[PDB]
Image (cartoon, coloured by chain):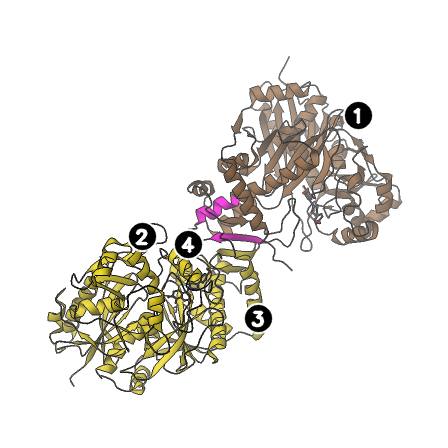
Chain colours: A yellow, B brown
């Protein structure tokens, strides 16, 4: 009696959404709203920040109204958590309260030249140079390099630089700013770790690097953890604070790939998960010891729950074309019309019958970092149908995530215990079979699959205390949200003929330049 | 001063047909009769000699019956030429006049063992040991290795040799034997050239080679030209003497591919034909004295008109997967369904935007002789589509020719003046234009696309004086029969780029064993 609810804003790359969870851990209201994907010249990608905040508020109030429709006693939400696309960086004015320009997105490639200035000059040829600090190579992806491009290239931004009006944030910062009404100006540690400006081990700003990299430290917010006060919601954008009825607090903020880690319950070391948006991200919890490169791979914050409380670390690898690849074979190549034709065409053959397909359309980017690798297929005979190609594309995804976990077993010094998985592609029986084989671990597939949203809610649910122990959290997720589970069923030298084929094919992929 | 008709028996691998041509090189009547493809053990292929003979006789009768039924001017046939599938070998008995067994076909692999034994035990391990006499490497194709194999496995054949009675013949010789009711036992120079028992420089049976391979020369027929009197028709095997009415001389005989060359009017040094069927066969006329190859190509007789008459020689290259690759795309891969769409989709993109597709399913048969080559695609992005892949296949078919033509130009010491085409894939104008642009010569396409049977008919009509010379034959064609014409039309820097991409792609094809 007296049912409690926490809210979460999943701000993504192509859309925004808000998801109300109960105390039993169920999404009970949801609403989605897209924003525009602006592409000036090839490789660029911008989002309108106002569009994002407007999206977030419409999600909010429409979701809240729907919960009332099905529970008329719902008076308020205890707290709101955030989670978001990371690296995407916003530029804004402190008293204009508003974007000086569109926000360049994580996978934009406008920063190409600025990356080479830095990796040559500041990095003395070594891209890794800053990596026992940031936990990251130098790339076009991370925040600081966007910040530069914006200080260099934008009339308004360079103008505001000097006048002391220039705030910079990741989307988590920018949401939490306008939501509170200009009141809050903070970031959580996981988001912070993406900026190329944080010290991974102290979880504090790196004044050597801000200075070395020519970004005025006063543009940055105060780092906090993922599970504490951040601001309050005081705005009426799309009737947002009126619909909340009480003043509700913001008590979770967390980067998206780490939000999926937390909400899949990967609290203990050697626990990992794999998300499928377009590509992939694989994240393993490594314990409290910050781990570092041997190959490439990323060192990042997993989650620090609470005021200076226990912090947890992780390694991160990407596959760049995963759900994309299945869609490419359909829309571009006409290999099959309907979605479940793919899964049944793959089953209609015993195996690849010789061939390998390396779905490296836009370079190769898990332990092997060849950006000249292109999409290649080798070993085809006249006895090769689309069924073999579809299966080979599936094998390839798992053969990459194999190489990734191998690298994780090295760098982390641990073994991979569990691997929970989630997305468009985790609803595919045959991949979670193959992958479970080639890696040789159980694989868990959650029936409450909204786990990235769940992550943030939990953070705010802990801070406000709808749950208090991670045992409580984990015990509800056992007594409620069903796992399906998938064992391995493939013999050591089936697996070694498949990797030997794989490593032989990888050699033939180098193409561009 | 009445209308005159030459007929052509065109005896092919899957089928036999008789075309009747008039004095304007118009095919004006045609029947076709298939024959049965017997295959005992995998990779064997074997035809029935008497069944092949009956088709030729039914084709004759029916075409003739249909012709007078619709040409009141048609009185008789002035002569008959024969064109045939080439290396295929028949053993029959002089007394019984009946085959001692079935006929092993050009692409049959039962000569594999013999082919290793002959390369090892007589060419020290060099397969080209006899190439300066025969024009040919040791391979499973050629007639002598089929003749030998029959002595070594078929007891009735060794039997016959002993008793004095045995004949071996290629199909031209066999047809011409039974068409004569056993009176003529002769073979033309072009067919003789594919036995591996003829000396190219003399065009006589090589006593050296017969001795070494241990085929007695009593089992071989008399070598004659392509155009002269071979015999008359004296059988009533499907009322063919009845249908024919008159005495009708057999005055033309020529191997199919050389029939094509001749029927495309390629009478000069540096003229070529490519037949775009399932695979490709290219034959250039190299001139009046042989040229030998250092690229794996075959030297061969092109044609020779008149007993003791000028003999023109040729180089020959093949490629293995042309129309087959189209078929594969369509029916193993579903990149389209209806034939017309292939060229409509290739046409729908400016080029291949970076990709190469080597359709090397059963290896590389052109002048780079890798059988570990397998089908590869390289260079795909998410902007790649079946349109591109398809165009890329056409490009590939075009790049192998270009490379084959190259070899021949080196070995022959001449430029290609002009390329005539035929075969189904000749009705794809996009391939044809990619092909002229690559080669920088116009490409000629005959509207009357019955060139293989026309070759046989010309030889027959020259010897009967229907036509009186090679300037006449070429004039009657130019006047009476239309010719499409396709001129080069692309930058020579796009040309270089494709060849460069082709070359890089080749270097990635290697997969088998
Ligand atoms: C010039 O040669 C190169 C040197 C370094 C790189 N990298 C830069 C991009 N970075 C991609 C990346 C890998 C990954 O494992 O996770 C990522 C990730 O999680 C992101 O959010 C963004 C980018 C990556 C890999 C190393 C590429 C080419
Ligand atoms: C690198 O060492 C070699 C590898 C293969 C060969 N071959 C040359 C003969 N070739 C057969 C062949 C080639 C061709 O270009 O056209 C042919 C052809 O037109 C036929 O009718 C039959 C056989 C061939 C297959 C094996 C020779 C040397």
| Number of the front mark, 2 or 1 | 2
Q: Residues within 10 Å of mark 1 (few under 14, many from 20)?
A: few
Mark 4 highlights which residue? Answer: B382
Cα–Cα gap, marks 4 and 2: 16 Å
| Number of the front mark, 1 or 3 | 3
Label number found at residue B308: 1
Label number found at residue A496: 3
Label number found at residue A39: 2
Cα–Cα gap, marks 2 and 1: 75 Å
Identify the subunit bearing mark 1. B
Q: Using the image as rendered, state which of residue A130 and residue B138 is in the foreground.
A: A130
Question: Residue drawn at (41%, 51%), measured in percent from left and top?
Answer: B383
Q: Residues within 10 Å of mark 2 (few under 14, many from 20)?
A: few
Classify residue B198 as left or right of residue A198: right
For numbered disc 3, what is the local secondary structure? helix
Locate residue A461, reporting x and y percent.
24, 80
Residue that extends furthest to the top in the rendered view of this protein = B1
Q: Using the image as rendered, state which of residue A350 and residue A375 is in the foreground.
A: A375
Residue A486 among magenta residues:
no
């Amino acid at each position: 009696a007296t049912m409690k609810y926490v809210g979460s804003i999943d701000q993504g790359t192509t859309s925004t959404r808000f998801i109300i969870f109960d105390e039993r851990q169920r999404p009970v209201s949801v609403h989605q709203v897209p924003h525009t994907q602006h592409t000036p010249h090839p490789g660029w990608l911008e989002h309108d920040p106002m569009e994002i905040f407007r999206s977030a508020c419409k999600c909010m109030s429409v979701a809240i109204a729907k919960l009332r429709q099905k529970d008329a006693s719902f008076r308020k939400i205890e707290a709101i958590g955030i989670t978001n696309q990371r690296e995407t960086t916003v530029a804004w004015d402190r008293v204009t309260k508003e974007p000086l320009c569109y926000a360049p997105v994580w996978n934009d490639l406008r920063t190409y030249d600025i990356t080479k200035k830095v990796t040559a000059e500041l990095g003395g040829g070594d891209s890794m140079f800053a990596s026992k600090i940031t936990g990251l190579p130098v790339s076009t992806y991370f925040a600081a390099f966007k910040m530069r491009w914006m200080l260099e290239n934008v009339p308004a931004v360079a103008d505001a630089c000097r006048r002391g009006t220039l705030c910079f944030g990741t989307i988590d910062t920018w949401l939490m700013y306008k939501l509170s009404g200009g009141k809050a100006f903070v970031t959580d540690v996981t988001n912070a770790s993406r900026t190329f400006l944080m010290d991974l081990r102290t979880r504090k700003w790196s004044p050597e690097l801000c200075e070395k990299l020519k970004i005025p430290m006063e543009t940055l917010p105060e780092i906090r953890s993922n599970s504490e006060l951040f601001g309050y919601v005081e705005t009426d954008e799309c009737g947002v604070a009126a619909a909340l009825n009480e003043r509700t607090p913001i008590m979770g903020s967390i980067g998206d790939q780490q939000s999926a880690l937390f909400g899949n319950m990967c609290f203990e070391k050697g626990e990992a998960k794999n998300t499928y948006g377009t590509g992939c991200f694989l994240l393993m919890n490594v314990g409290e010891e910050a781990r570092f490169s041997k190959h490439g791979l990323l060192s990042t914050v997993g989650f620090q729950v609470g005021r200076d409380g226990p912090c947890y670390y992780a390694l991160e690898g990407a596959i760049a074309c995963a759900g994309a690849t299945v869609e490419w074979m359909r829309r571009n190549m006409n290999l099959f019309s309907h979605i479940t034709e793919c899964e049944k065409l793959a089953r209609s053959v015993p195996g690849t019958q010789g061939i390998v397909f390396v779905p490296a359309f836009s370079g190769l980017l898990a332990p092997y970092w060849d950006p000249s690798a292109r999409g290649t297929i080798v070993g085809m005979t006249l006895k090769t149908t689309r069924a073999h190609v579809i299966r080979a594309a599936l094998q390839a995804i798992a053969l990459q995530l194999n190489d990734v976990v191998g690298s994780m077993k090295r760098d982390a010094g641990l073994n991979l215990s569990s691997l929970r998985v989630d997305g468009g592609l985790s609803k595919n029986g045959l991949l979670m079979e193959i992958q479970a084989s080639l890696l040789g671990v159980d694989i868990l597939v959650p029936s409450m699959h909204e786990t990235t949203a769940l992550g943030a809610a939990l953070c705010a649910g802990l801070a406000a205390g709808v749950w208090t122990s991670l045992e409580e959290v984990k015990a509800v997720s056992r007594r409620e949200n069903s796992w399906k589970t998938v064992s391995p069923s493939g013999s050591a030298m089936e697996r070694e003929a498949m990797i030997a084929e794989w490593r032989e094919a990888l050699k033939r992929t180098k193409w561009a330049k």
